[PDB]
Image (cartoon, rainbow over all chains, first blue to last red):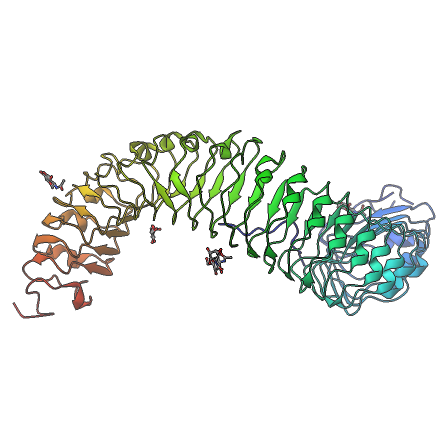
Length: 12
Length: 577
Ligand SMILES: *[C@@H]1O[C@H](CO)[C@@H](O)[C@H](O)[C@H]1NC(C)=O
Ligand SMILES: *[C@@H]1O[C@H](CO)[C@@H](O)[C@H](O)[C@H]1NC(C)=O
Ligand SMILES: *[C@@H]1O[C@H](CO)[C@@H](O)[C@H](O)[C@H]1NC(C)=O
Ligand SMILES: *[C@@H]1O[C@H](CO)[C@@H](O)[C@H](O)[C@H]1NC(C)=O
Ligand SMILES: *[C@@H]1O[C@H](CO)[C@@H](O)[C@H](O)[C@H]1NC(C)=O
């Protein structure tokens, strides 16, 4: 299954 | 020597979303010691590996990734004693990983990322003394990390992210002398980061986030120079950020968001001159932001929102000519907005809402050519919203509500080319709406409510894309313009709590989609046009506290809330006629 990478996508 | 390169008459057709073994298996019974590389990746194949692959005894390269292979791992591959790289990633292999990888003594690359494996990570692999890359991410692996994986000298890349591993992180892993890349987040690890990790002097990339970690951040990891990527977000770290972290001279990306960190951003952060991305969202941080962060030569992303920072924003922020997005919403910042934020025209997202910024919107912000989303409500910004925003070619979302803006409303808003949302509610303007506000091309939501507006509502010329209009709670006098049927996309209109006189515009009834209408607390007079009862789309029509007369319509008005009225008489559905 896929796994997230990179910084936190959270935004406003 | 793959895709039937050397015959090793017979087949060259390795395609056709067919299944392996038997479409395969002939490939192997061409016994041959001629075959050193076999690449069956992305052929849409499905199944098991045949026993007979053991006869490709000279194989060095085997890549079966990106198919639909299933069943448990085939230990026949462990008989390929010359195998040097093995790529099994993105398949459907399941069950506990079987023992016996040891016999692949010269194995240097093993990628099995994205599978269906369960059980414990194979302790057997700690015996591959030449291995350099190991990728077991993306399955359903359980248990702890085998402390013996720390004997994998030579190893420079390890990926185990995205399983259901847990326990404490094994201190012994810190002896992987040559490890450059460690990605092990998205698990359930608990406890702290072992301080022995401070010996991974070659480490460039360190994840382990969205786990269950806790404790103070270990001061010793300031020792990790060379490190460029440090992600530890979505954990439970408490305490303050080590001031030892100012020694990570190579760090480009830092992300501590979603923990419980306390105290201040260490002022040594002002020395991390390679920082590209600084993100500390959703912590308990406080104090002031070190001025030198506004001088970082390469900073592109600055996320500080949902903390409780005090003080002013660094005067020179943006002067590096590189800022792209900044978001410091939900803090206690004060002072003015720096003029340099968009130097370079790279800034496209500027988020400042829920602070206590003071002063005039800097006029430099009107020449920010790249600006796209601007959210600055709930502050103390005063003066005249400057003129020039309507000349930005990509500005689509603007929220300046709940501030202290006075005098007039910039007229160039109405000629902004792509502006889609504009609020401006709650502000103290004491002047008229701009004459050509409804002209605007794209502009779906406009909400200048409780902004001390005065005068008449301009004629609804054009009104191309509006679907929500909020002007409630001002002192708009005069008549509701009778050409409102130009607003064909309108869904919600609120003109309540004004000083509007006259009749209800009958052209409201040229309603393809109007759903919510609020005209209450005005001075309207006349009937509700009985044609309103034909609207198959009005669900709210609050018109109470007015001076209307006559019957209420029927049809699709017969099941509306009686409270929506409070003026005089109406169709049998209240006080008979
Ligand atoms: C396996 O094949 C893919 C492309 O199909 C390639 O990107 C990948 O690097 C290969 N694996 C190895 C270990 O070379
Ligand atoms: C940020 O605001 C959210 C609501 O928007 C609130 O739950 C949170 O506690 C706030 N945190 C800080 C540190 O300001
Ligand atoms: C944030 O800090 C200051 C006190 O110095 C004040 O704005 C407020 O009380 C604090 N907020 C929270 C949620 O503690
Ligand atoms: C506009 O801003 C006000 C106050 O800042 C807010 O309460 C309202 O929901 C906003 N309107 C829209 C349509 O977003
Ligand atoms: C209300 O409208 C009339 C239109 O003639 C105008 O004269 C009057 O000044 C308006 N009220 C204001 C601006 O407070």
